[PDB]
Image 1 (cartoon, rainbow, N blue to C red):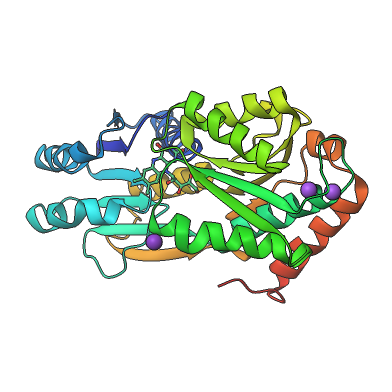
Image 2 (tube, rainbow, N blue to C red):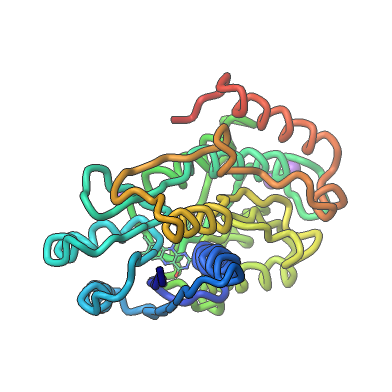
Length: 314
Ligand SMILES: Cc1cc2nc3c(=O)[nH]c(=O)nc-3n(C[C@H](O)[C@H](O)[C@H](O)CO)c2cc1C
Ligand SMILES: [K+]
Ligand code: NA
Ligand code: NA
Protein backbone atom coordinates (compact mmCIF):
# COMPACT_ATOMS: atom_id res chain seq x y z
CA UNK A 1 0.00 0.00 0.00
CA UNK A 2 1.22 3.49 -0.88
CA UNK A 3 1.61 6.03 1.92
CA UNK A 4 1.71 9.87 1.73
CA UNK A 5 3.02 12.05 4.53
CA UNK A 6 3.08 15.82 4.94
CA UNK A 7 5.30 17.85 7.25
CA UNK A 8 3.98 21.28 8.21
CA UNK A 9 6.89 23.48 9.25
CA UNK A 10 5.64 26.48 11.29
CA UNK A 11 8.39 28.73 9.93
CA UNK A 12 11.41 27.60 7.90
CA UNK A 13 13.34 24.34 8.03
CA UNK A 14 16.91 25.63 7.70
CA UNK A 15 18.53 27.39 10.65
CA UNK A 16 15.78 26.28 13.09
CA UNK A 17 17.04 23.29 15.10
CA UNK A 18 13.62 21.88 16.01
CA UNK A 19 12.38 21.99 12.41
CA UNK A 20 15.66 20.90 10.81
CA UNK A 21 15.66 17.87 13.13
CA UNK A 22 11.97 17.18 12.44
CA UNK A 23 12.40 17.22 8.68
CA UNK A 24 15.68 15.28 8.75
CA UNK A 25 14.08 12.49 10.80
CA UNK A 26 10.90 12.23 8.72
CA UNK A 27 13.04 12.15 5.56
CA UNK A 28 15.30 9.47 7.01
CA UNK A 29 12.30 7.21 7.69
CA UNK A 30 10.73 7.85 4.29
CA UNK A 31 14.02 7.27 2.40
CA UNK A 32 14.60 4.09 4.39
CA UNK A 33 11.23 2.57 3.64
CA UNK A 34 11.25 3.70 0.00
CA UNK A 35 14.44 1.67 -0.39
CA UNK A 36 12.45 -1.50 0.35
CA UNK A 37 10.45 -0.91 -2.83
CA UNK A 38 7.50 0.77 -1.22
CA UNK A 39 5.84 3.87 -2.68
CA UNK A 40 6.01 6.67 -0.14
CA UNK A 41 5.27 10.30 -0.79
CA UNK A 42 6.61 13.13 1.36
CA UNK A 43 5.63 16.78 1.01
CA UNK A 44 7.21 19.43 3.27
CA UNK A 45 5.30 22.70 3.59
CA UNK A 46 7.21 25.68 4.96
CA UNK A 47 4.59 28.01 6.31
CA UNK A 48 6.95 30.92 6.89
CA UNK A 49 6.82 33.39 9.76
CA UNK A 50 3.22 34.65 9.45
CA UNK A 51 1.44 32.79 12.23
CA UNK A 52 -1.96 34.16 11.23
CA UNK A 53 -1.92 31.91 8.16
CA UNK A 54 -0.90 28.67 9.89
CA UNK A 55 -4.39 27.45 10.74
CA UNK A 56 -5.80 27.90 7.23
CA UNK A 57 -2.73 26.25 5.68
CA UNK A 58 -3.16 23.20 7.95
CA UNK A 59 -6.89 23.12 7.21
CA UNK A 60 -6.15 22.99 3.47
CA UNK A 61 -3.71 20.09 3.99
CA UNK A 62 -6.39 18.17 5.90
CA UNK A 63 -9.01 19.07 3.31
CA UNK A 64 -6.79 17.63 0.53
CA UNK A 65 -7.56 14.21 2.04
CA UNK A 66 -4.42 12.70 0.72
CA UNK A 67 -2.00 12.47 3.66
CA UNK A 68 -2.10 9.47 5.98
CA UNK A 69 -0.38 11.73 8.52
CA UNK A 70 0.39 15.42 8.84
CA UNK A 71 3.43 15.97 11.07
CA UNK A 72 4.34 19.22 12.80
CA UNK A 73 6.13 20.59 15.87
CA UNK A 74 5.99 23.25 18.61
CA UNK A 75 3.74 23.78 21.59
CA UNK A 76 1.30 26.16 19.87
CA UNK A 77 0.25 23.54 17.32
CA UNK A 78 -2.48 21.88 19.41
CA UNK A 79 -4.25 25.24 19.76
CA UNK A 80 -3.78 26.01 16.06
CA UNK A 81 -5.28 22.61 15.26
CA UNK A 82 -8.37 22.80 17.51
CA UNK A 83 -11.04 23.62 14.91
CA UNK A 84 -9.33 21.47 12.25
CA UNK A 85 -9.55 18.38 14.48
CA UNK A 86 -13.28 19.07 14.74
CA UNK A 87 -13.86 19.75 11.04
CA UNK A 88 -11.67 16.94 9.67
CA UNK A 89 -11.82 14.19 12.33
CA UNK A 90 -10.53 11.50 9.90
CA UNK A 91 -7.22 13.36 9.40
CA UNK A 92 -4.42 12.03 11.60
CA UNK A 93 -1.90 14.50 13.03
CA UNK A 94 1.41 13.95 14.86
CA UNK A 95 2.98 16.92 16.67
CA UNK A 96 6.37 16.79 18.41
CA UNK A 97 7.41 19.32 21.05
CA UNK A 98 3.76 19.64 22.11
CA UNK A 99 1.19 18.37 24.57
CA UNK A 100 -2.44 17.63 23.75
CA UNK A 101 -3.89 14.96 25.96
CA UNK A 102 -7.31 13.52 25.12
CA UNK A 103 -7.69 14.33 21.48
CA UNK A 104 -8.90 11.64 19.05
CA UNK A 105 -6.87 12.30 15.89
CA UNK A 106 -3.79 14.04 17.33
CA UNK A 107 -0.85 12.27 18.94
CA UNK A 108 1.77 14.44 20.67
CA UNK A 109 5.21 14.03 22.23
CA UNK A 110 6.73 16.60 24.60
CA UNK A 111 10.32 16.58 25.88
CA UNK A 112 11.15 17.23 29.51
CA UNK A 113 12.50 20.71 29.05
CA UNK A 114 12.86 21.30 32.77
CA UNK A 115 15.68 18.75 32.51
CA UNK A 116 16.91 20.18 29.23
CA UNK A 117 17.07 23.78 30.44
CA UNK A 118 18.31 22.92 33.95
CA UNK A 119 21.26 21.12 32.38
CA UNK A 120 21.94 24.24 30.26
CA UNK A 121 21.65 26.64 33.18
CA UNK A 122 23.88 24.59 35.46
CA UNK A 123 26.58 24.40 32.78
CA UNK A 124 26.20 28.11 32.06
CA UNK A 125 26.60 29.06 35.71
CA UNK A 126 29.68 26.83 36.12
CA UNK A 127 31.28 28.62 33.17
CA UNK A 128 30.21 32.07 34.38
CA UNK A 129 31.62 31.39 37.87
CA UNK A 130 34.93 30.07 36.50
CA UNK A 131 38.13 31.78 35.42
CA UNK A 132 37.75 30.79 31.77
CA UNK A 133 38.99 33.32 29.23
CA UNK A 134 35.69 35.20 28.77
CA UNK A 135 34.17 34.63 32.21
CA UNK A 136 33.76 37.67 34.45
CA UNK A 137 33.29 38.14 38.21
CA UNK A 138 29.53 38.78 37.97
CA UNK A 139 26.93 36.01 38.34
CA UNK A 140 24.90 37.01 35.31
CA UNK A 141 23.79 34.81 32.41
CA UNK A 142 21.37 35.53 29.57
CA UNK A 143 18.67 34.01 27.43
CA UNK A 144 17.52 35.38 24.07
CA UNK A 145 14.17 34.01 22.95
CA UNK A 146 12.55 34.38 19.54
CA UNK A 147 9.18 35.08 21.20
CA UNK A 148 7.56 34.61 24.59
CA UNK A 149 5.21 31.65 24.93
CA UNK A 150 3.97 29.53 27.84
CA UNK A 151 6.58 26.78 27.58
CA UNK A 152 9.33 29.40 27.44
CA UNK A 153 8.04 31.37 30.45
CA UNK A 154 6.79 28.47 32.59
CA UNK A 155 9.37 25.78 31.83
CA UNK A 156 12.50 26.83 29.98
CA UNK A 157 13.30 30.14 31.72
CA UNK A 158 12.56 28.94 35.28
CA UNK A 159 14.49 25.70 34.76
CA UNK A 160 17.50 27.59 33.28
CA UNK A 161 17.47 29.85 36.36
CA UNK A 162 17.08 26.87 38.72
CA UNK A 163 20.03 25.07 37.14
CA UNK A 164 22.18 28.21 37.52
CA UNK A 165 21.07 28.77 41.11
CA UNK A 166 22.07 25.20 41.99
CA UNK A 167 25.62 26.40 41.33
CA UNK A 168 25.24 29.66 43.29
CA UNK A 169 21.90 31.12 44.51
CA UNK A 170 23.12 34.61 43.53
CA UNK A 171 22.88 33.81 39.80
CA UNK A 172 20.55 35.92 37.72
CA UNK A 173 19.12 35.31 34.24
CA UNK A 174 18.50 38.31 31.97
CA UNK A 175 15.84 37.41 29.39
CA UNK A 176 15.52 39.28 26.09
CA UNK A 177 13.15 38.70 23.16
CA UNK A 178 13.73 39.19 19.43
CA UNK A 179 10.12 39.22 18.27
CA UNK A 180 10.66 36.70 15.46
CA UNK A 181 12.57 33.53 14.64
CA UNK A 182 14.82 34.80 11.83
CA UNK A 183 16.43 38.22 12.33
CA UNK A 184 20.05 37.61 13.35
CA UNK A 185 20.82 41.34 13.30
CA UNK A 186 18.25 41.94 16.03
CA UNK A 187 19.37 39.04 18.22
CA UNK A 188 22.96 40.28 17.90
CA UNK A 189 21.78 43.69 19.17
CA UNK A 190 20.29 41.98 22.26
CA UNK A 191 23.48 40.01 22.80
CA UNK A 192 25.52 43.23 22.78
CA UNK A 193 23.15 44.79 25.35
CA UNK A 194 23.53 41.70 27.58
CA UNK A 195 27.32 41.68 27.25
CA UNK A 196 27.57 45.29 28.32
CA UNK A 197 25.28 44.55 31.31
CA UNK A 198 27.84 41.94 32.44
CA UNK A 199 26.47 38.70 30.97
CA UNK A 200 29.27 36.28 30.03
CA UNK A 201 27.23 33.20 29.00
CA UNK A 202 24.05 33.37 26.86
CA UNK A 203 21.56 30.83 25.55
CA UNK A 204 20.01 31.70 22.16
CA UNK A 205 16.63 30.12 21.45
CA UNK A 206 15.63 32.27 18.50
CA UNK A 207 15.73 30.01 15.44
CA UNK A 208 17.55 31.48 12.46
CA UNK A 209 18.43 34.45 14.67
CA UNK A 210 20.66 32.14 16.75
CA UNK A 211 23.49 32.92 14.36
CA UNK A 212 23.43 36.58 15.46
CA UNK A 213 24.20 35.56 19.00
CA UNK A 214 27.12 33.38 17.80
CA UNK A 215 28.42 36.36 15.77
CA UNK A 216 28.21 38.62 18.82
CA UNK A 217 30.01 35.99 20.94
CA UNK A 218 33.00 36.09 18.57
CA UNK A 219 32.82 39.87 18.25
CA UNK A 220 32.72 40.69 21.98
CA UNK A 221 34.06 37.58 23.70
CA UNK A 222 31.42 35.63 25.62
CA UNK A 223 30.21 32.03 25.78
CA UNK A 224 27.13 30.34 24.36
CA UNK A 225 24.93 27.69 25.92
CA UNK A 226 23.42 26.03 22.88
CA UNK A 227 19.97 24.39 22.90
CA UNK A 228 18.05 21.66 21.07
CA UNK A 229 20.79 20.11 18.89
CA UNK A 230 24.57 19.83 18.73
CA UNK A 231 25.92 23.37 18.26
CA UNK A 232 29.58 22.98 19.32
CA UNK A 233 30.99 23.27 15.79
CA UNK A 234 29.00 26.42 15.03
CA UNK A 235 31.50 28.47 17.04
CA UNK A 236 34.32 26.27 18.35
CA UNK A 237 35.48 27.37 21.77
CA UNK A 238 32.56 29.78 22.24
CA UNK A 239 29.84 27.15 22.50
CA UNK A 240 30.37 25.58 25.92
CA UNK A 241 27.36 23.28 26.05
CA UNK A 242 24.66 21.63 23.96
CA UNK A 243 21.52 20.68 25.91
CA UNK A 244 19.37 18.82 23.47
CA UNK A 245 16.16 17.07 22.49
CA UNK A 246 16.42 13.91 20.38
CA UNK A 247 13.96 15.23 17.82
CA UNK A 248 15.64 13.76 14.72
CA UNK A 249 15.42 10.28 16.22
CA UNK A 250 11.89 10.68 17.56
CA UNK A 251 10.65 12.04 14.22
CA UNK A 252 12.30 9.09 12.44
CA UNK A 253 10.84 6.55 14.89
CA UNK A 254 7.28 7.85 14.78
CA UNK A 255 7.27 8.28 11.02
CA UNK A 256 8.36 4.66 10.68
CA UNK A 257 5.54 3.58 12.93
CA UNK A 258 3.09 5.41 10.70
CA UNK A 259 4.47 3.81 7.55
CA UNK A 260 4.22 0.33 9.07
CA UNK A 261 0.72 0.91 10.44
CA UNK A 262 1.70 1.04 14.10
CA UNK A 263 1.26 4.70 15.07
CA UNK A 264 -1.68 5.26 17.44
CA UNK A 265 -4.27 7.88 16.49
CA UNK A 266 -3.97 9.75 19.78
CA UNK A 267 -1.97 10.06 22.97
CA UNK A 268 0.29 12.61 24.70
CA UNK A 269 3.72 11.35 25.72
CA UNK A 270 6.45 13.05 27.74
CA UNK A 271 10.03 11.89 27.20
CA UNK A 272 13.07 12.94 29.21
CA UNK A 273 16.62 12.08 30.21
CA UNK A 274 15.72 8.69 31.70
CA UNK A 275 13.95 7.76 28.43
CA UNK A 276 16.93 8.79 26.30
CA UNK A 277 15.28 11.75 24.56
CA UNK A 278 16.83 14.70 26.44
CA UNK A 279 20.64 14.78 26.71
CA UNK A 280 23.59 16.96 27.49
CA UNK A 281 26.20 16.29 24.81
CA UNK A 282 29.44 15.42 26.59
CA UNK A 283 30.87 13.15 23.91
CA UNK A 284 31.82 15.84 21.37
CA UNK A 285 35.58 16.43 21.20
CA UNK A 286 34.96 20.18 20.99
CA UNK A 287 33.32 20.10 24.43
CA UNK A 288 36.26 18.22 25.89
CA UNK A 289 38.66 20.79 24.35
CA UNK A 290 36.57 23.87 25.24
CA UNK A 291 35.53 23.26 28.84
CA UNK A 292 37.97 22.63 31.72
CA UNK A 293 37.97 19.50 33.87
CA UNK A 294 36.29 20.79 37.05
CA UNK A 295 33.27 22.02 35.10
CA UNK A 296 32.98 18.81 33.07
CA UNK A 297 33.25 16.71 36.24
CA UNK A 298 30.37 18.59 37.90
CA UNK A 299 28.23 18.51 34.77
CA UNK A 300 28.70 14.70 34.53
CA UNK A 301 27.78 14.29 38.19
CA UNK A 302 24.59 16.26 37.59
CA UNK A 303 23.68 14.07 34.64
CA UNK A 304 24.06 11.02 36.88
CA UNK A 305 21.65 12.44 39.50
CA UNK A 306 19.03 13.05 36.81
CA UNK A 307 19.57 9.65 35.20
CA UNK A 308 18.89 7.92 38.55
CA UNK A 309 15.83 9.96 39.54
CA UNK A 310 17.68 11.22 42.62
CA UNK A 311 17.17 14.67 41.15
CA UNK A 312 13.74 14.51 39.62
CA UNK A 313 12.66 17.51 37.65
CA UNK A 314 9.03 16.74 36.79
C1 LIG B 1 4.63 29.80 17.96
C2 LIG B 1 6.04 29.27 18.02
C3 LIG B 1 6.90 29.40 16.95
C4 LIG B 1 8.23 28.89 16.95
N1 LIG B 1 9.00 29.03 15.88
C5 LIG B 1 10.30 28.60 15.91
C6 LIG B 1 11.14 28.74 14.83
O1 LIG B 1 10.76 29.30 13.78
N2 LIG B 1 12.42 28.32 14.91
C7 LIG B 1 12.90 27.68 16.02
O2 LIG B 1 14.08 27.28 16.02
N3 LIG B 1 12.09 27.50 17.09
C8 LIG B 1 10.82 27.97 17.06
N4 LIG B 1 10.03 27.78 18.15
C9 LIG B 1 10.64 27.20 19.37
C10 LIG B 1 10.66 25.71 19.48
O3 LIG B 1 9.38 25.22 19.24
C11 LIG B 1 11.18 25.32 20.88
O4 LIG B 1 10.30 25.78 21.86
C12 LIG B 1 12.58 25.85 21.16
O5 LIG B 1 13.41 25.55 20.10
C13 LIG B 1 13.15 25.29 22.48
O6 LIG B 1 13.13 23.87 22.49
C14 LIG B 1 8.72 28.25 18.14
C15 LIG B 1 7.82 28.13 19.22
C16 LIG B 1 6.52 28.62 19.17
C17 LIG B 1 5.64 28.43 20.38
K1 LIG C 1 3.12 32.42 30.23
NA1 NA D 1 30.46 35.55 35.49
NA1 NA E 1 33.87 34.21 37.22
